[PDB]
Length: 82
Image 1 (cartoon, helix red, strand yellow):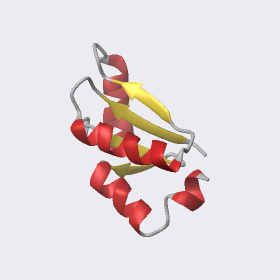
Image 2: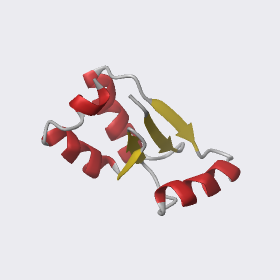
Image 3: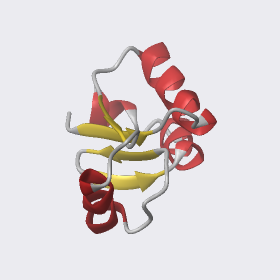
Image 4: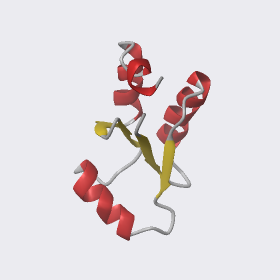
């Protein structure tokens, strides 16, 4: 599954999403913005937001933890990730 999450040093909702994904025990990628700028610009073209957490599930930009956790709440996260 193609899963990516942009993050930073101080992002409580990043920790929220990652804690759920580690409870599910899925395989995902993390993308730090900590000192970054060129891949933060990448996140402009990708997300159209430039804020975090911003999860992408099978390259599909979901949005943040609440958006992701809703995708889990509908049982729709699992058939993409697992």
